[PDB]
Each structure stands twice: as structure tokens, then as C-alpha cells.
Length: 58
Image (cartoon, rainbow, N blue to C red; front, top):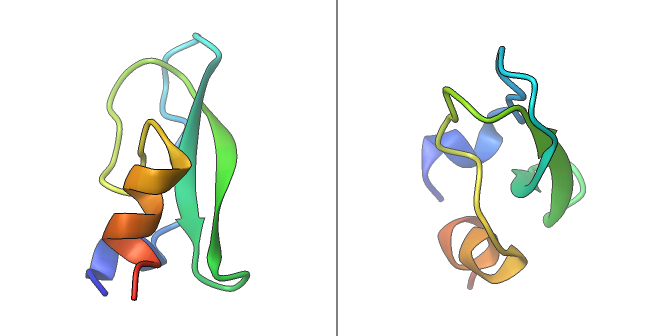
């Protein structure tokens, strides 16, 4: 799978509370994390499905 699927979730420096999904390489599934509103990294999806297609899909 893409290398970014292995990266930890990144909240970033902004102060919003936006629920996003990240692929947790250890657990093997997409979990929610709190994104701050700016400077998102690639392991950040708006739905579990987008997250699964990118990283868990097989």
C-alpha cells in the first residue's frame, strides 16, 4: 500500500476540532482522529471508505 498509510495521524497546529479518518497500520483499520483545520498530511480522509480504498482495500 502507499507509504503514507504507515504514517501516524497529524492534528497539525490549527485549533479546530474536525473528525477525520487515518489508517492505523498496526490495527489494520481506519480510525477517527481530531484534525485541527490546517496542514493536513496524506493519511487523512473524510470517510472510512476513502481511507479503506487508499490503504486497507484488497
